[PDB]
Image 1 (cartoon, rainbow, N blue to C red):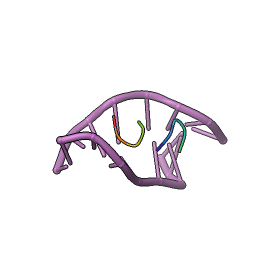
Image 2: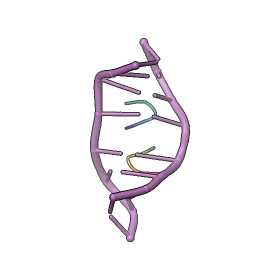
Image 3: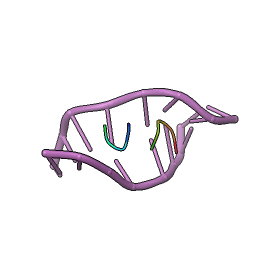
Length: 10
DNA sequence: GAAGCTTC
DNA sequence: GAAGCTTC
């Protein structure tokens, strides 16, 4: 997830 | 070494 | 079913 906690996605 | 899925 | 990286 995030940054932070890619995206989602990529 | 963990805690955190939504682009197709 | 990848799969893109960070904040702790």
